[PDB]
Each structure stands twice: as C-alpha cells, then as structure tokens.
Image (cartoon, rainbow over all chains, first blue to last red; front, side, top):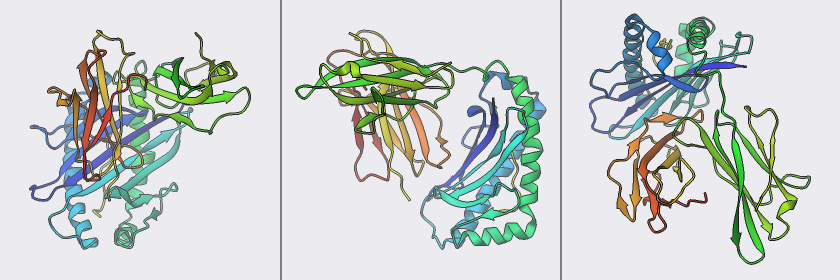
Length: 276
Length: 9
Length: 99
C-alpha cells in the first residue's frame, strides 16, 4: 500500500501570442485532484475530485497565488531558454515540470522528484539525493551553475521532505474511501477466423483500475513473443481501463492456448481460454 | 500543496 | 522535436447494434501539445465531440481522450482523424468493434 503525489506543470509559447498558456495538474496516487489553467476567465486552482471540496477558501486563494507565481516563473524561464539555445522569435516552445513525492506503505518518504523538460526533452533534474543536479545539454549547464550557486536544491528538498509529505498525508485521510479501492479485470476470449486453417484468439480485460496490467499467452508451458499482438492500455472513459492481447493459432488446436491476466486487484492471476 | 520554484532557469 | 500521435478508436462498452454507447478516440505519445482531433461518422465530422483536458505522461509526451455518444449499427462506419505537425498528412483510424 504505497502512495504518491505529483504536480505536472506546462507552459507553452506560440508564435504571435502575447504570452504563454500555463497549466498545472495535481495528482494523488496517480488520480487528478486539482487543476489550474491560465486560459480560464478567472484563472484559479479548482477541485477535480469530490473529496477536495473540504478545503476552505484560504486553501484555494493560497494555491492560486502560487500558480500565478509559477506562471510568471515559467514565462521568464521560457525567455531565458530561447536565449540559451539561440532560438529566434516566431516558433513554438514548451517547458514542463514534474515534481512530487513517493511514500512507502509506512507513510515514510521513499523518494523525491523534481525534473524539467524543454521541447519535450530532459533539461535538468534533481537527483535522488536531493542535493545535486543532472543536466545533459550544454545549454542546460548555464541553469545548473546558476542553481548550484543559489542553493536551489536545498529549497526543493525542504518542500519534498516537508510540505509534500505532510500535505499528502492530509489528502490520504480526506479521500480515504475514494482512492483506496481497485477494480478487478473481468476477462474473456473471443474467436476470430482468418487465412485458411488459422484463427486469432483475443484475450480481453475490461473494467479494471488502476491501469497497470499484464496479459500473457501460453502454449501449455512457455509464454509467447512469437507475434503476440496487443494494444496499449486505454481508458474506457468512466475511470476504468481496457486491454487486449492476441495470438495466431491453428484451427482445432485452440484449447492448447491459455491466457493469463495479472492485476493488483486479483487475489491470484486469472487463467482463461476460448469457450464455444 | 504545490511547489513554488526558486531561481529561474 | 516532434513525436507522432498513436491512436486507438474503441467503444466504452461492449458494442451491440442498436444500443447507445460511447465511442472513444485515445491519442497518446505526441509533441508538441497542439493537435486537432475529429471523430467521423461515414466520412463526416461528428459535431459535439467531448474532449478531455491536455495532460502529459512521465516520458513528457502528451495525451488526450476524445469521445462521443453513438449508437453502433451494422452499416455505419466510425473513425478518428488526427492532424499534428509530426505528420505531413492527417492520420485516420477506423473503429473496429473486435479491437
């Protein structure tokens, strides 16, 4: 029973637009719970799960001012980065940030996170020690030296060990019914004839949460990389997820094939096969 | 509770 | 630099002809975040398509879920058409009820 919190932040500059659009999204255990967007009429952080309406107006006023601060920080940084990469006016650019904490099932901090990307690529990141920085790009070295000289790492470390953990604990108590549960996958196999003397067996899994899942096919023993087709896990749109995996099989010898579904809601892996 | 950033890039 | 969108088109519920349902178009793994997504019935734009908010994955790439109400039939065909700077031309994928 581990836990996590993240804020995913994005600022996008576009050619003629006056100034960048800034979006921040907060997540508790990988579920969205707050959101700010500078394109709204009255830009404010907003609840995105029912359990967050417990928070009084001082919570929302403070987080909103923080967001407006972040917006200005991303605006100046975008400007600085344009100069660092000798990019000219008239293009589109992106600055992103992930930050947050992971807790063990004892609710102790497992790991802190602080990373940035520019144009969708690693720019700079705080290492797991919460003291040193990784920056690959020559242009990013300028930021690394600046942040090393100002003691930025100490500032982010205090947030990640302090507030991030403290307020995550408070959120986990407040939403203890909503995001404790999981939905087990319900699975079935469909049959689909094809090119003479062969058929595809499609193993479906439906209605599961969270998204993490594995579907394997077995020829009475070993797995199958031998053209096992599959799809990426996809949202149903109602909070659950879907996935399938398939394998080409001789017609008649289809009961030598078994599909297994591995999901954290299951008491044990499901085993399954085609049934007329 | 969201982070607030330190020095700009 | 550009990451090309991966697209899946599928229904929320098991498809049954004549039964209201929701058609999804899940667009993932793209950069930059500007993108046009249309869902199509028989070649033609479906007018009131719901669009989730811009999000991104831990690899930094963006993703979106477009969806709409629909009632599948034997004869109508559905699809999703994505325009993005990573592609010279739009990409269409067709709803297949068995996938």
